[PDB]
Amino acid sequence: MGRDEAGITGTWYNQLGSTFIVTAGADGALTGTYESAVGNAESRYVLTGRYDSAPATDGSGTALGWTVAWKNNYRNAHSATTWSGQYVGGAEARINTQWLLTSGTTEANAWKSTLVGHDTFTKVK
Amino acid sequence: MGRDEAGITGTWYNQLGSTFIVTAGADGALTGTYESAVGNAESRYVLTGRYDSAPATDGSGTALGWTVAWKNNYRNAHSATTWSGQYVGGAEARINTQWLLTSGTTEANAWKSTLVGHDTFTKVK
Amino acid sequence: MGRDEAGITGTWYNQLGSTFIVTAGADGALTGTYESAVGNAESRYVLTGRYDSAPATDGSGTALGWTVAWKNNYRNAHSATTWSGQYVGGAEARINTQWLLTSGTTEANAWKSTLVGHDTFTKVK
Amino acid sequence: MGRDEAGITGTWYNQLGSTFIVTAGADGALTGTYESAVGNAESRYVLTGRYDSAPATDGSGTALGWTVAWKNNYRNAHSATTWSGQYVGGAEARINTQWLLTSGTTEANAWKSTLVGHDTFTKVK
Ligand SMILES: CN(C)c1ccc2c3c(cccc13)C(=O)N(CCNC(=O)CCCC[C@@H]1SC[C@@H]3NC(=O)N[C@@H]31)C2=O
Ligand SMILES: CN(C)c1ccc2c3c(cccc13)C(=O)N(CCNC(=O)CCCC[C@@H]1SC[C@@H]3NC(=O)N[C@@H]31)C2=O
Ligand SMILES: CN(C)c1ccc2c3c(cccc13)C(=O)N(CCNC(=O)CCCC[C@@H]1SC[C@@H]3NC(=O)N[C@@H]31)C2=O
Ligand SMILES: CN(C)c1ccc2c3c(cccc13)C(=O)N(CCNC(=O)CCCC[C@@H]1SC[C@@H]3NC(=O)N[C@@H]31)C2=O
Image (spheres, rainbow over the protein chains, first blue to last red):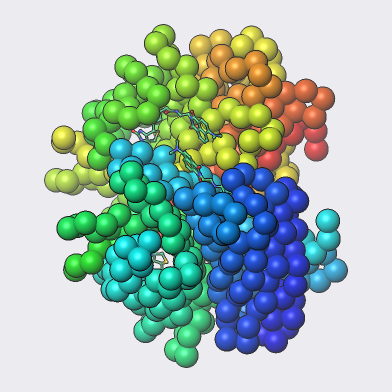
């Protein structure tokens, strides 16, 4: 709860070397910035999202998600990613996610508008 | 741009009868509430997300995404959904999305933590 | 069972105008050809897959999936799609699917190797 | 080509401890069996799929996919999984996949019919 808040807030790194900095609010909000090590991305981008401010205490992870639109002062990649996953606490804390990356397309190209992938975030690296 | 802002802001309905009410901010923010016609959901839930405040003008859609954590004053479904998609404007304006719904799980059950689906939102119904 | 076999076997069409011709075997096999109305595709491509030869009889759909590699005598698109979904029988019989389309990539590009989408197949159109 | 055939054919293991045994045919076929270490699964299940019998030689992976219906002599889990991904050869050869697992459902429950995940297969473990 406040446990999750404290667990989630901070800097995370994924397997690609991207950096996710986030504050979890007591109200279930996630707010922060994201810097992608790959793709059409430079510097930091705003992120917002939500999390289960009251997960179970049977050892279950904590559900959460967030979005980045790939526009900032330096680039506009006409796209947006959402990550959906769960926070697991402890000595090797992790956010395990799957993500959808959608590009704005013509109607003709809409069938190929969305990439899918997975990112695992840790507190080190 | 301001076009997208004006296009996106408002009430949308999906094929299931769910209701998405959203304000698009000039800064690329999405803020609002979501009421799901199905699943472990009651009343409205906070939503936040982002959108490409400056899509292309070659007739491409506008990328966007948002999250809902399935906790409010009435229920806690220990889960969170992200929708990723694009807004298409005009007489039959649409937000075409794919979504990931993750439940908090034990580590044993993490492989089955995430549902995937698609929702199409329109301004009527 | 033999019901499913009879239900599934035949020609289906999706919302894009693609054509899926399939034989369901008594052993749970699916075999046939696919012709895509869109993308880097021409003529027919082999398809194979499986289905639950013994679904429930509580009105549940019948789970199934199949793959196409996008290589034939005319083109090689260095890619393969899998469709996962369920057959629903009756007067407006449907196969409702989600699909993953993966392209062979460099290791650098693997994070963007896979598109996701949804196709609905019917017996007419 | 024959390279891919030789690369792919054999026994693979994923991070969960599941075992995938496959023969790649010269015609682009994949045929074999799958034994899942997790879920509603026992013993081996038939699998079929396809692969790009002629990938590029710029170091790109080889696209492929396959399906398992979760019915055999011991169990019927009313479901089917498709894996979509790419084979990468060499000293630490890998098949990197994403998967869709669909359960037969009522029409009411169709929105939650499909799980999504990722599996990485290697030749050892
Ligand atoms: C239609 N058709 C041929 C395309 C043409 C162009 C594009 C696409 C795209 C998606 C789907 C198809 C196309 C797409 O997303 N785009 C925009 C790309 N946008 C970007 O590169 C922004 C960085 C995204 C980084 C990802 S987020 C998940 C992962 N985790 C990380 O930390 N980093 C990676 C295109 O141009
Ligand atoms: C591990 N294993 C056996 C499960 C056990 C329980 C659950 C799950 C879930 C996901 C995956 C597996 C399980 C899951 O999400 N859950 C929480 C469900 N949470 C909810 O029902 C909240 C409403 C979500 C409504 C969806 S959002 C996309 C779509 N579009 C709409 O407008 N409405 C629908 C479980 O309990
Ligand atoms: C890495 N990065 C920038 C890409 C560059 C090139 C490509 C990709 C792809 C996928 C992901 C990224 C890229 C991809 O799949 N490719 C191959 C495309 N392959 C094809 O076009 C084959 C037809 C597929 C038709 C689809 S199947 C689901 C749907 N349902 C239907 O009936 N028809 C549609 C690329 O080139
Ligand atoms: C609708 N609602 C509440 C559900 C109720 C029951 C079920 C579901 C399912 C999917 C989605 C929702 C539900 C589902 O798939 N099912 C069948 C499960 N079927 C099985 O357990 C078969 C083993 C699958 C093993 C996976 S394959 C990807 C991964 N990689 C591996 O090597 N092993 C794992 C349900 O019962």
